[PDB]
Length: 73
Image (cartoon, rainbow, N blue to C red; front, side, top):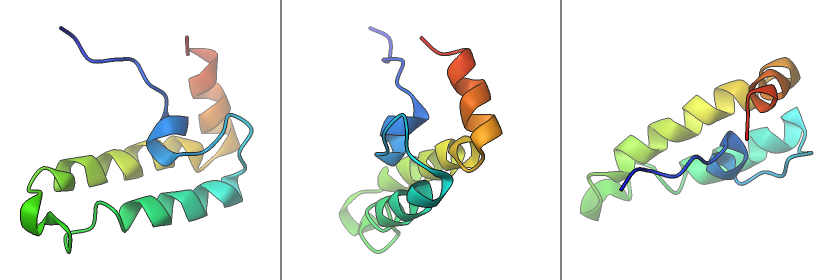
């Protein structure tokens, strides 16, 4: 009954070959989905919105993204 082990790639909606530039767009478009303007009927969306910045942080740098993939499954 545990949670699945997904990667930042999915949290941002970007491929495994995506670029630091393409991630910026996917990160922004996603944020608009979990924005506080749509939290009117989704008080949990705020928690998900944070996950975007968390994953985008690592995917924001090739080194961080690659390093994270090294310890991936």
